[PDB]
Image (cartoon, grey):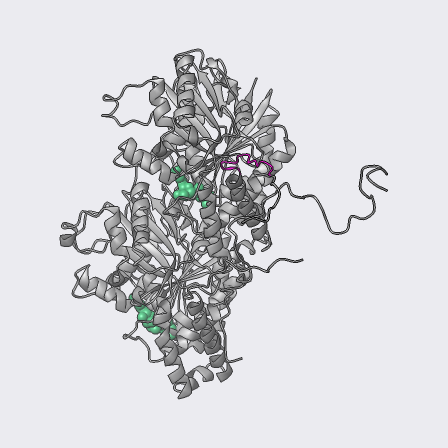
Amino acid sequence: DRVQSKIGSLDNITHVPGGGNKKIETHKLTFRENAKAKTDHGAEIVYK
Amino acid sequence: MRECISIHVGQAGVQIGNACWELYCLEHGIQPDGQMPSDKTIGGGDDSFNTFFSETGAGKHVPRAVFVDLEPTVIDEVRTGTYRQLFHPEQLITGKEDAANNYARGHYTIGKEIIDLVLDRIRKLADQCTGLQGFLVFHSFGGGTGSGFTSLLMERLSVDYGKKSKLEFSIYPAPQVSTAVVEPYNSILTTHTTLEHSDCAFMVDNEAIYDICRRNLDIERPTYTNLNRLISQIVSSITASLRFDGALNVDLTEFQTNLVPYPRIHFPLATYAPVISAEKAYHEQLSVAEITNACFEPANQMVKCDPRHGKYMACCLLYRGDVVPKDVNAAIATIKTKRSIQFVDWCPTGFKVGINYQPPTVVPGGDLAKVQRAVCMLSNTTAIAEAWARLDHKFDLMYAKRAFVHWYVGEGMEEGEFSEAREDMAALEKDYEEVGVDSVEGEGEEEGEEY
Amino acid sequence: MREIVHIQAGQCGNQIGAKFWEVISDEHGIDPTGSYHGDSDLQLERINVYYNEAAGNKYVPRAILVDLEPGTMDSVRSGPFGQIFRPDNFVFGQSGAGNNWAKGHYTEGAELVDSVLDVVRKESESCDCLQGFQLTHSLGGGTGSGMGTLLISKIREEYPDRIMNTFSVVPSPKVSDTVVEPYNATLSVHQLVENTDETYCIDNEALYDICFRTLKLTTPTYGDLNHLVSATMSGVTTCLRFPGQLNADLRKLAVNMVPFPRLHFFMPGFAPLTSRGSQQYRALTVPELTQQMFDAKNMMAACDPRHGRYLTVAAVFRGRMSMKEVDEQMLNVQNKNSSYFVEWIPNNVKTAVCDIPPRGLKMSATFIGNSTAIQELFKRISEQFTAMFRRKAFLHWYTGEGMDEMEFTEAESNMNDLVSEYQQYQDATADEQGEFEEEGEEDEA
Ligand SMILES: Nc1nc2c(ncn2[C@@H]2O[C@H](COP(=O)(O)OP(=O)(O)OP(=O)(O)O)[C@@H](O)[C@H]2O)c(=O)[nH]1
Ligand SMILES: Nc1nc2c(ncn2[C@@H]2O[C@H](COP(=O)(O)OP(=O)(O)O)[C@@H](O)[C@H]2O)c(=O)[nH]1
Ligand SMILES: [Mg+2]
């Protein structure tokens, strides 16, 4: 194999900063991409 | 309550063993007959000496250690020296003919006859442990007992003690000085074998401690009996928490949690300070930072590969006697402010620390310095790459010319083994270069927005 | 009546612990062998807060004393007051940690755990109303830090309406005494932030500058730093044990200190801090306490709190003194240093006042702060964790006691969220706009 290093010197180099995370915010926020049926909202006057 | 083993292999091991055991006796107040008629104590039980000595029904202590070379002579010397009655008769283990500086005598064709007789003595010392902590094993790379059998024993300890710490203490090859012509086969055949069976592997260099002895101990005639007495001050300082109570204790299995960043990167270099003569000791007040800064000078290292040619990466830094944690705090930070002392940017946590109340003893043999406080240190660095850069090309030259290979082969080996050992030592060459990489930045990389 | 258990674990936790049970033993006239011979009957009169009563008028602390090695428990029992403790409470193991938090959390500390819980049950089934449990432990160390995580987790599951308090020794701005302290710290924050009610952050660098620059100790020892922590423990727990104008227990601190059950890591302080010649050339008043106690050097973790905003404060003052004066000074700080505090919290400070000062003092004050200024410490842990983790360094020990490598990012994402959470509430005002109209466009420019 013509020899190489054996230590895991950079094994996590695919991950990146940081140093913060999110933040949780008023503009959505509980949703998911497949929660079907149960149409809005609001009775037949607003509207059906 | 807790216990450990010491093991002394080849003519380098058995002799650094005397210095260490000379000291430990003297440090604990144990005599050359194993008695301690020494302190008018009223309480007792720890007595942390029991970690290193076995007590006898009528108060003699016996060292928890084992000796080996493959001829008697170096052992007959202890056996008839001042510690005859001190050391346990059956822990002093002997062959007939020595391994000749041939690894294959030590690992393979001779080794095989006394390995299980050592292991029997060692299982019979675990039956005296109340909790076997680990093993501290003393040799040299240049001896063929010191290389071959130390690496046989590490094969065998890494099964019978597969969880416990196997800690080595090498005389490592000097840069310009040598003690065998077959020095490179030994160094690499042992290092390739222990590179999966040992936990840590600390280095001292005779070419380095000779100059410390002429320069700063101010001695004209540094013998191996004097130099092994200086090496003993590192061993007593590294074990202090397991010998005495202290402001900040360290465990047998703590060094490697802090010093070995990746399991193959296990070559921390060793040192002591302050090294003075008694007449110099009078022109130094020796405050904690003075010892610390001195302990960081390149010409003050007990390995002669210069730290000017590498980055530091992991330290453990150990203080004895009269010492204030606030002085340690500042003096450590002083060395980090001096980032001129080159260190890897990606380990600012580069230190572990330990502070022990018990001051050092000198083994008398000259005028005595009136010591108050002392420092010892283990450092992992890429200067070790500067050391190995030659020992490696020496194995390339020897092996290309096939010089001496018929002694080793005849006595239990095949050329394919000389290839594998060197191949892994070429991987290890890239390993101490990978820990020299100034790493790339990861900040400010993103995917762009989905529509 | 109202009982607390104390736990002490690893080396800094047992050493701080043997200043606590020296300081409080002495504050109560407890003898070095567990006799009582004290000089005010008030001392004896709420003794059960911290003690058991044993035969022949002997007294036993609710100390639980834990370790993975046998030496600190020799050095505490050979040590002063080592005879007040009960022998069945000395549950130390046989392995160390050797700074490995996972040797704590997954293997060896997990092997002691049932035997530590055995004395946690004994002591708590022998209380009449346990409030809580106090832990002196490490954070960047291992023997305390990795026991403490699992111990709090099981306690939180056996005792879930009892209070949970932690005296943690935090990694310092210039030095480390352990290399894996970022590992030891991040991992710990994940585990604790779900199960503590209170964590104190206590810095040896912040206490050294106190001890050397304000107390003028020529030689600051751990013995002298631990005197300060035990003064702190004593101080915030005075009203449980003695009469006072305004009494407050740990559940009464909690409710003023804790705006969201995530945001409960704090900085402490004590006052007065005074050198021996300065004791002549200073005069002790409630304003003197007040001045010194919001002063940037008096802070027992390594921040100037003017870098952020106080959300909540507590002040615990001991001795005989005007409740007018202490309201007044607290008003003055809140109004002449009003920008030190966050404004979406009004009137931001709890105060409580006890009639009994520290045995060696005329009067004293003890502060606790919740501030957005100490995020710099968690930023430091997050970056210094990254300097190890981005390279896989030291990870092979944790995985060798059999932790999962993914859990590192689970704790790191939590820390990175937590440090963002203190930052997003910093000067977290409301902002408002007015609606806008226009006139008609015309041909003329
Ligand atoms: N510092 C120091 N090193 C020593 C001492 N004795 C031997 N050595 C080292 O150990 C080697 C010399 O001793 P050897 O005779 O080779 O030891 P050995 O392992 O018994 O040799 P064989 O068994 O014959 O292979 C060299 O590598 C030396 O540098 C000693 O007292 N002091
Ligand atoms: N203030 C204080 N710090 C201590 C004391 N003992 C140790 N420390 C520090 O506390 C931290 C953790 O030490 P230790 O408890 O030994 O770690 P562990 O045993 O691995 O949990 C490091 O910063 C130590 O230097 C002590 O008596 N007081
Ligand atoms: Mg030999």
Taking depth in this image into account, of B250 and A35 the one nearest to the observer is: A35
Q: What is the x, y in percent for residue B42? A: 35, 33
Q: Quick check: can you spot residue C30?
A: no
Q: Is residue C271 above or below residue C444?
A: above
Looking at the image, residue A21 sits to the left or right of residue C242; the answer is right
- Residue C400: quadrant of the picture: bottom right
Q: What is the x, y in percent for residue B297? A: 26, 59
Q: Is residue C426 magenta?
A: yes
Q: Is residue B239 above or below residue B181?
A: above
Taking depth in this image into account, of C300 and A35 the one nearest to the observer is: A35
Q: Residue furthest bottom?
A: B401
Q: Is residue B202 magenta?
A: no
Looking at the image, residue B72 sits to the left or right of residue A12; the answer is left
Main SS category, magenta section: loop
Image quarter where ligand 2 lies: top left
Give the quadrant of the C terminus of chain B: bottom right
Magenta-highlighted residues: C425-436
Looking at the image, residue C171 sits to the left or right of residue B277; the answer is right
Q: Count numbered badges in the picture.
A: 0
Q: Quick check: can you spot residue B395?
A: yes
Q: Residue at x 39, y 47 (%)?
A: C177
Q: Residue furthest front?
A: C444
Taking depth in this image into account, of B116 and C350 the one nearest to the observer is: C350
Q: What is the x, y in percent for residue B363? A: 24, 53
Q: What is the x, y in percent for residue B234? A: 32, 56
Taking depth in this image into account, of C25 and C148 the one nearest to the observer is: C148
